[PDB]
Amino acid sequence: GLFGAIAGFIENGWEGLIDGWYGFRHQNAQGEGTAADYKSTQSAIDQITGKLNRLIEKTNQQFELIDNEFNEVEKQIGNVINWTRDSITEVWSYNAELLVAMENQHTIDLADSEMDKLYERVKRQLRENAEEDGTGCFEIFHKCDDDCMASIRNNTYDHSKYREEAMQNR
Amino acid sequence: GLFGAIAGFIENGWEGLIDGWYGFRHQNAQGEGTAADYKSTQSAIDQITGKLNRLIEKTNQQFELIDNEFNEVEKQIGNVINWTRDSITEVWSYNAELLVAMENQHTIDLADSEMDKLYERVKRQLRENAEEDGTGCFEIFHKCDDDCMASIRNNTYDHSKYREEAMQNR
Amino acid sequence: GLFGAIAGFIENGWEGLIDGWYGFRHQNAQGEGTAADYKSTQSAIDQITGKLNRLIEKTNQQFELIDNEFNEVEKQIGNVINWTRDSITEVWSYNAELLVAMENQHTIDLADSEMDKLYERVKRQLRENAEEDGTGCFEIFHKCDDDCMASIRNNTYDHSKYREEAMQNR
Amino acid sequence: DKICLGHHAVSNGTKVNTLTERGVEVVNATETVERTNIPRICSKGKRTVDLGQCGLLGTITGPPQCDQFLEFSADLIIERREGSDVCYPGKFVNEEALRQILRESGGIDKEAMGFTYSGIRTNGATSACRRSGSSFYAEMKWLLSNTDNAAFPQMTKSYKNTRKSPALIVWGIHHSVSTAEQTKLYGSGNKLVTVGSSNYQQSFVPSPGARPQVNGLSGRIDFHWLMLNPNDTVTFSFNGAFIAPDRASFLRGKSMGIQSGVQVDANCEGDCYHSGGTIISNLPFQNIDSRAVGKCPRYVKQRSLLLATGMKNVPE
Amino acid sequence: DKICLGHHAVSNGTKVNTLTERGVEVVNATETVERTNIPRICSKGKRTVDLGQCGLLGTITGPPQCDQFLEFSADLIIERREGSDVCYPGKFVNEEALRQILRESGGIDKEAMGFTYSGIRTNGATSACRRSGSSFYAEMKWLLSNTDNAAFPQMTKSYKNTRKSPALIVWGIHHSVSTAEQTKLYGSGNKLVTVGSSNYQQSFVPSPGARPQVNGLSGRIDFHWLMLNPNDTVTFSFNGAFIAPDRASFLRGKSMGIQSGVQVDANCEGDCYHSGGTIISNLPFQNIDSRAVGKCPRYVKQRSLLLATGMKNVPE
Amino acid sequence: DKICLGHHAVSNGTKVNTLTERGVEVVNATETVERTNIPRICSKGKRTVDLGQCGLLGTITGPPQCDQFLEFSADLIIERREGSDVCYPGKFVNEEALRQILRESGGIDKEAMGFTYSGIRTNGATSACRRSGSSFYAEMKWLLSNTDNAAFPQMTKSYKNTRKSPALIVWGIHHSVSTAEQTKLYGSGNKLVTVGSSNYQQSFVPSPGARPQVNGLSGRIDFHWLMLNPNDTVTFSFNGAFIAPDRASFLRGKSMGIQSGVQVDANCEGDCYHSGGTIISNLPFQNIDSRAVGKCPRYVKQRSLLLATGMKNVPE
Ligand SMILES: CC(=O)N[C@@H]1[C@@H](O)[C@H](O[C@@H]2O[C@H](CO[C@]3(C(=O)O)C[C@H](O)[C@@H](NC(C)=O)[C@H]([C@H](O)[C@H](O)CO)O3)[C@H](O)[C@H](O)[C@H]2O)[C@@H](CO)O[C@H]1O
Ligand SMILES: CC(=O)N[C@@H]1[C@@H](O)[C@H](O[C@@H]2O[C@H](CO[C@]3(C(=O)O)C[C@H](O)[C@@H](NC(C)=O)[C@H]([C@H](O)[C@H](O)CO)O3)[C@H](O)[C@H](O)[C@H]2O)[C@@H](CO)O[C@H]1O
Ligand SMILES: CC(=O)N[C@@H]1[C@@H](O)[C@H](O[C@@H]2O[C@H](CO[C@]3(C(=O)O)C[C@H](O)[C@@H](NC(C)=O)[C@H]([C@H](O)[C@H](O)CO)O3)[C@H](O)[C@H](O)[C@H]2O)[C@@H](CO)O[C@H]1O
Ligand SMILES: *[C@@H]1O[C@H](CO)[C@@H](O[C@@H]2O[C@H](CO)[C@@H](O)[C@H](O)[C@H]2NC(C)=O)[C@H](O)[C@H]1NC(C)=O
Ligand SMILES: *[C@@H]1O[C@H](CO)[C@@H](O[C@@H]2O[C@H](CO)[C@@H](O)[C@H](O)[C@H]2NC(C)=O)[C@H](O)[C@H]1NC(C)=O
Ligand SMILES: *[C@@H]1O[C@H](CO)[C@@H](O[C@@H]2O[C@H](CO)[C@@H](O)[C@H](O)[C@H]2NC(C)=O)[C@H](O)[C@H]1NC(C)=O
Ligand SMILES: *[C@@H]1O[C@H](CO)[C@@H](O)[C@H](O)[C@H]1NC(C)=O
Ligand SMILES: *[C@@H]1O[C@H](CO)[C@@H](O)[C@H](O)[C@H]1NC(C)=O
Ligand SMILES: *[C@@H]1O[C@H](CO)[C@@H](O)[C@H](O)[C@H]1NC(C)=O
Ligand SMILES: *[C@@H]1O[C@H](CO)[C@@H](O)[C@H](O)[C@H]1NC(C)=O
Ligand SMILES: *[C@@H]1O[C@H](CO)[C@@H](O)[C@H](O)[C@H]1NC(C)=O
Ligand SMILES: *[C@@H]1O[C@H](CO)[C@@H](O)[C@H](O)[C@H]1NC(C)=O
Ligand SMILES: *[C@@H]1O[C@H](CO)[C@@H](O)[C@H](O)[C@H]1NC(C)=O
Ligand SMILES: *[C@@H]1O[C@H](CO)[C@@H](O)[C@H](O)[C@H]1NC(C)=O
Ligand SMILES: *[C@@H]1O[C@H](CO)[C@@H](O)[C@H](O)[C@H]1NC(C)=O
């Protein structure tokens, strides 16, 4: 995608993440654990379902018979009708093909974008108390226990508390 | 939007910014002040007006009467015409709806993008003489007087002059 | 473009880069040199050719004559046909114009994106052993000889080897 | 020591198409083209009239198979292959235009024209039109000359539409099996029938001769029609060979008409119909029948167009 | 201590629609569908011909209400509800096709056919066509038999289009009020009129009888027409019942034609017209009238489609 | 000291259009609208029939210029301006509908109708139809009365389509140059021809009179036609003025038909044709001819629409 995270600087997805779309998997002095980011998940879900409600609707526009299956209409007028209908089929087959293709492009880029938005939020939270690994990972110098990690996920991590510690541990 | 600044890591817009689209509001040892970034404003404005000139135009294609309000044409040929016209209405009503929707998506993302482009320019200007707050703010360690702040807005801030100072003030 | 690199924080392109689309031009204690990034080049090329194969195709849909160049059909039915054909021309002329415009927008943004993706990869490789110049350049504190520079281009630059050195040279 | 960001993935993903690429795999997707048909006519909540053996045009003239359809009312009208518009062999001029009017008529209501006659017979019948022995079209009258070879006196009859909506008028022309058999019924000489409304002028001369035996009979009746506006008058001048309307029809309102070979189903609701049944769907497109009518998804040639509803699948 | 980046916002924003979302609020927006009608025909700079009481087809035959339109010139032709194509009751075969030709003719220029006659009368008139007492169609001649019940001699007349553009030829057929009143004018027997051009063959037999009294008269005239190519010849064989062309028409160039019930306005300029007036707009779409003609925005069913011209509004 | 990232650029770039901007310069681009025409009909691999001087409808009746086309076979049928459907002056009723049927017929195969005659002549000819002296239409028979002014006896002839596909039936009506010259050939009185198939009823009375001299001759023949379904019967009742079919046609399969003035070329392959030649292209659009037929790029009014195939050009 356009934002280079999904199928980009993140190697792959997590089949274990059944909890949501995007999430965290930490490592610390207590072991490994994983969880889901509700907010980023929701934006993506909501935007995608917004596409659907918009597309999954039929028009209230009635069309009637202008030819006849049991009793063929005069050939001349019949050929004009067929040509007109076929012309209209060509327009709609084109439209549907372009619609779905361009929707899918945006969908995929949009989901990539949201992952990037989540990554960048966290980076900004940690400040100079962490570093960019490059695989979609933040190496933390100070000791983040499970309590610490949960503060990050909840947008409450206070960087000033651990600043001195992690700046020294460079 | 896709770039996560507007209605993203920036909390909200400024109703006081009547001067342009994007801008700066600094705080220092002399008090608070605000101003507008002409360049970023202009790119957005120019791109948007570029959409309009392209869309706000009518075709030079003439169409004539093929039926009659005062003297109804023969019913068969009349029903083919009506069906054809209604079919064409359906195509254009679809087109207009898709056009505006997809234009608006791009418009909104484009305006988000330009804000991100402005933010990133400044970050790059300051280098290790500043830090990312996370609300769309740069905390500056050394003393930027009003003279200092104007140098940033004009792309002339020399980071090397204040480097030693702000690196120490970490 | 949307990602602000090409015709953005990079000043201009390189006419000397005949080797590929995106690339590196280093400076060091041995002199200046240049080379091409295959991976980023390929993604852009592949995505663009993917657009083409999709668009450069004709339909298998046959259409036949419904009027006559050598012997004009009855005027009424003739005017309905002409009006119908002209209506269809208007739809397709619109479609082609919108298709190419929106494709080109995406193309240009996509190529901008790939340049940004390449820039960000490298930044992440170097870590705190380098800094953002702002013109699309990385000032390196430690001595990268030609051997060093090639390690970056090949995704093998070990930052830990030179970390102590460049952190000191701040 | 660390914290890593990621996203979800599946073993089974769905391939879709984009601007740039054919068959990129995504987490989840959904169909945009309908292929599921319901093989019934879904009529729930709709005043429905299945014409069966009655032809739509026969509702106006009234051969025996249309006796229970002379004044129908409907939102939905269904024609069947087994239907027939005639008992005595013949057909309608501008047949399809009339059908179209009738498909969306909302049904019909019939009213006596008020023609009376003198110096001629009014009760002509045949073995093709069966109602306890020989009969004719219920809404028409087969006009003759009192006795054989007798001069059919040149006649003038008018009818003013006094109602607020247009009247549908229908009259027949009888082409006998020979030049002789024409003079028997209506007397010799060149017969002439003419018709004149405010926006309608036409004339009708007969044409006796030998047609193939349909229903065992080689005679034909040409049915013709016009829409008579409110307050407008219509006059019939005829020397013979004329099948006279007894009643005029008026259109009740709105309806739709379809052709089909499947059963009606009142448990089922739908607005998009075709000869094989009902397309019930909210999908914007369908690949079932390009001649489907009513309120329908747009027909497209593609069997399938999957729309991504998830991010790109990038598994282990 | 700090410097913060931001963007502008408003208290009043405008809601618009996107791919993803209904009614997202933006800073500014603009309409893409035109709803503003001008209730006049905007004719500034255009040679305009308002037919008023003259019917378009009457410009070819010339009943009195079209006397000042026999040779008009125009870029824009306007038909009115009060218009009428006839003085003596009757109508045209292929009426609408002819109108279409005439709407874009650029107007007409008339030229004498050069028919002369012998053994018959040429000055037939009526009370329906009024020019200081009884008259006829200015461009036609009502041909008779010299005296009552006299044999109308079988006649042959030709006309070669010597000009470089196709000639429009028009001739009438008179259907008298009875079989008797036909023989009076043209003598007894079966009258026959035929017409033959390089790509046109047709025949016309009359049909006397009683039509309703239009203009107080129960007779009718059937007008017919063909386009005679350059250097091509057209011949008329007739035993009677024939209304002869005196002049042929040629088409001047280009024009457009509209139908409308509003006034002309030369202060006003426009290229998109409909019966209620003029659509002046640069917007790509319109929701005023799907039958608008000229150079127009595309008709759409939506009243409104707002296009974002600003960023998303995100106020305090 | 440093390492810098960049991208490629050119001195010569190509300007293209976007959503936002007209004429932004990119590295490389490619055309989407075809303008290159091949001025030949590209027929490689296709059974092709160039009718030349034979008119398509003349393949059914058989004037001399169509003698080598009476039973053709084809995927591709070409009509030429010099073509003519008739030898003896005349034309077809519903001419264009018939052409359309024949363009996609795949060609024709002919079969004897099996009509025989008694009390009349069957070998009528003319100087307009030349085959070593005077001849007629190869697939037809000009039916007369044995001797001059003799009564043409009212005749009944039938033909059952025993085959599994619909039969194309064609018959003519002869309009002599005068009322006298009609009675000579077929005897005096009002001649009547009628035709009756399961879904077809019509009648045909002649119309003698003076048409302009085409091929030096002032007579005309009206050709008429129907499609006779499998197992259906068709009957002809005629007092005279009748040109009888000798053979019926059946349609072989599928084909396409074009009109053109350029040469055939078997070295060349294409599926999109127009009167000036062949459009060979994979581009999705074309700006050559809006009436092109076959399998074609969509016609658009733009000469050119360049599609970016490279990044934006941003040189020194
Ligand atoms: C009763 C009589 O006078 N003659 C009888 C013959 O007609 C009959 O031959 C049969 O004739 C049949 C046609 O008969 C009708 C019909 O349509 O059934 C009878 C209708 O009354 C008559 N109606 C009118 C208004 O004239 C109708 C009409 O003349 C024609 O349809 C006009 O074309 O004809 C049918 O052709 C049978 O196949 C044929 O055998 C014989 C044998 O029953 O008996 C005679 O007494
Ligand atoms: C003068 C004369 O010989 N007879 C007078 C009666 O005709 C007249 O009755 C009135 O007849 C009216 C119809 O008259 C015209 C017409 O169209 O106005 C007169 C035209 O000269 C005649 N033209 C030709 C070429 O024949 C025309 C034509 O015959 C018919 O239109 C053909 O259908 O008829 C009209 O019907 C009146 O309503 C009717 O009273 C009486 C009364 O005035 O006086 C007689 O002297
Ligand atoms: C041989 C004879 O009895 N009379 C000769 C005159 O006919 C002839 O005058 C010329 O007549 C020409 C028309 O002749 C045909 C034709 O179409 O060529 C001859 C056909 O046999 C005849 N066919 C039938 C079935 O009747 C045909 C037909 O009658 C008409 O086409 C029907 O409209 O006419 C042609 O008009 C010449 O221009 C004309 O001079 C003279 C002069 O050669 O000699 C007579 O002996
Ligand atoms: C117009 O197209 C219809 C099909 O959409 C043609 O009708 C079909 O004809 C084929 C072969 O002739 C039959 O197998 C089918 O039974 C027909 N289908 C339907 C739905 O009618 C029709 O022939 C075409 N019209 C003309 C004038 O050729
Ligand atoms: C085709 O559609 C037109 C409308 O676009 C129909 O004409 C309208 O008919 C309604 C009701 O019959 C009237 O109230 C209006 O006065 C008509 N409007 C116009 C603009 O003419 C017309 O009936 C349709 N054609 C056929 C054959 O049914
Ligand atoms: C329908 O449009 C065609 C053109 O697409 C018209 O035919 C052209 O007419 C012009 C001027 O009359 C001629 O110069 C050309 O030779 C014609 N071109 C072709 C391809 O035929 C045609 O007149 C229009 N139909 C009607 C009924 O007006
Ligand atoms: C899922 O996997 C199964 C493997 O048996 C395959 O047959 C099926 O088509 C797949 N369905 C999906 C991805 O919806
Ligand atoms: C995936 O999409 C389908 C639509 O085809 C939907 O019914 C289903 O709920 C979705 N499943 C998941 C796990 O999102
Ligand atoms: C029809 O005529 C009657 C007069 O009896 C009148 O009341 C009515 O308004 C007329 N209606 C129309 C539509 O002309
Ligand atoms: C602006 O606000 C007023 C509040 O009175 C509202 O009525 C109006 O619709 C708004 N108009 C806009 C946003 O254009
Ligand atoms: C907002 O858009 C409208 C178009 O509807 C335009 O007339 C106006 O100038 C714009 N106003 C501002 C403040 O941008
Ligand atoms: C018409 O005929 C004349 C001969 O008098 C000739 O000069 C002219 O070129 C011809 N024009 C056409 C179009 O046939
Ligand atoms: C390239 O440059 C030449 C300069 O002579 C110009 O004429 C030509 O149009 C250009 N062609 C391109 C960009 O394809
Ligand atoms: C540029 O595009 C054209 C298509 O018009 C193609 O033929 C050519 O190979 C391309 N050239 C380069 C250098 O990419
Ligand atoms: C036509 O009739 C014959 C009987 O001779 C029969 O075998 C055949 O099935 C029939 N075909 C059709 C299409 O009616």
Image (tube, coloured by chain):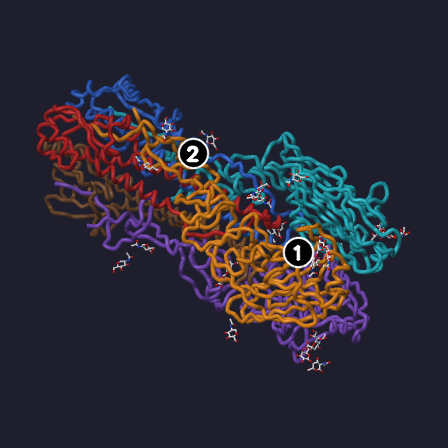
Chain colours: A brown, B blue, C red, D purple, E cyan, F orange
Q: Which chain carries label 1?
A: F
Q: Quarter of the image containing the C terminus of chain B?
A: top left
> Which is more foreground, mark 1 or mark 2?
1
Query: What is the number of the mark on residue F127?
Result: 1
Q: Distance between the residues labelled 1 and 2?
A: 71 Å
**Residue under circle 2?**
B51
Q: Quarter of the image containing the N terminus of chain B?
A: top left
The x and y percentages for residue D77 are 56, 64
In the displayed structure, would residue F171 be above or below residue E278? below
In the displayed structure, would residue A15 be above or below residue E275? below
Ligand 3 is within 8 Å of the C-beta of the residue at disc 1: yes
Residue at the extreme right of the image, as rendered = E147
In the displayed structure, would residue E84 be above or below residue F66? above
Q: Is residue C54 left or right of residue B133?
A: right
Please tell me which residue is depicted at 59% across the width and 71% down the height of the picture.
F114
Q: Is residue F211 left or right of residue F80?
A: right
Tell if the residue under mark 1 belongs to the same chain as the one under mark 2: no
Please tell me which residue is depicted at 83% across the width and 51% down the height of the picture.
E144
Q: Can residue D52 be seen in this view?
A: no
The x and y percentages for residue C133 are 21, 25
Please tell me which residue is depicted at 14% across the width and 38% down the height of the picture.
A140
Q: Which amino acid does label 1 sit on?
A: Ser
Q: Mark 2 lies on which chain?
A: B
Occupied quadrant, residue E18: top left
Residue at the extreme front of the image, as rendered = F132
Packing grade of label 2 (10 A; few <14, some 14-19, many >=20) is: many
The x and y percentages for residue B108 are 37, 36
